[PDB]
Image (cartoon, rainbow over all chains, first blue to last red; front, side, top):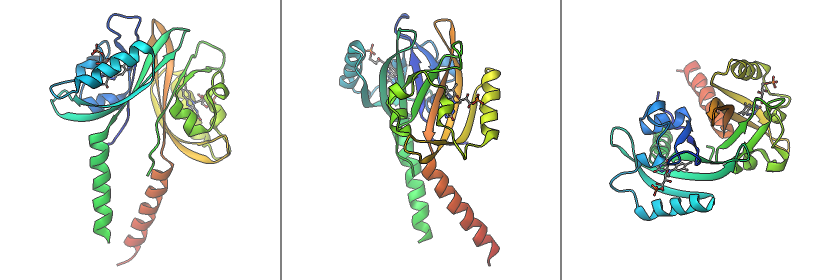
Length: 125
Length: 128
Ligand SMILES: *[C@@]12=NC3=[C]C([C])=C([C])[C]=C3N([C][C]([O])[C]([O])[C]([O])[C]OP([O])([O])=O)C1=NC(=O)[N]C2=O
Ligand SMILES: *[C@@]12=NC3=[C]C([C])=C([C])[C]=C3N([C][C]([O])[C]([O])[C]([O])[C]OP([O])([O])=O)C1=NC(=O)[N]C2=O
């Protein structure tokens, strides 16, 4: 119970709207969506009210150009909780066919947990 | 604690000895091998003296069963230094074909820290 784990997705851009075709349990736990509530969707489903449209634009462009991209973007869990998602996307090839691998980091949580350790270690003196 | 990128590897178990067909830069950085020195190999090439056969067994069994697995296993960089690899492998299906995807997290500093806190807890408790 309660751990920080990276989220990993693979999407298939040869399919309609570049859907997620693989997701790790880390991302299930990070976002609050079950595996089958993630698979088959475009990753944009995690965006919401305060997602910066300019950074969404910059992802779209990167993916169009098959350029690796890293960006911090506001994302939303199934229960509505906002989190900062540090997203790295890598274009890649498997069957001499292109896929995208995304690695997601819950920066909000990584900070929260590092501070708990920080504050604990203080309390020891 | 550890502050490095995670490694991702994809293998194709339909090819002989389940070779690596994709590796990200996170794993290049972590292992000290360039992509050209990784692709086409089996991931076991990162193992060495202190790699516990029990954990190798755990991985071998899960892949044979086509089931997810997580282990903490000792691996080695090209320069010979040992790192602790918290390794998660899932099967996956891409365009109706099966592959494995592996996620590698360097937990060497966390393990060092855990050991010290564990020792201190043991020591505190032995006292009054
Ligand atoms: C989602 N991560 C993610 C991972 C990969 C491998 C890829 C290809 C995309 C994402 N997205 C971005 C999203 O799918 C989309 O590409 C962008 O919104 C831009 O395109 P549109 O059509 O919307 O203009 C990710 N988006 C997220 O918000 N969070 C991530 O984890
Ligand atoms: C290697 N990671 C890794 C990633 C994937 C996707 C797969 C399928 C395997 C690995 N391995 C395990 C290794 O290749 C092998 O399966 C095991 O050694 C068990 O089989 P054998 O024949 O050797 O008994 C990984 N092994 C590692 O040591 N480090 C990883 O990062």
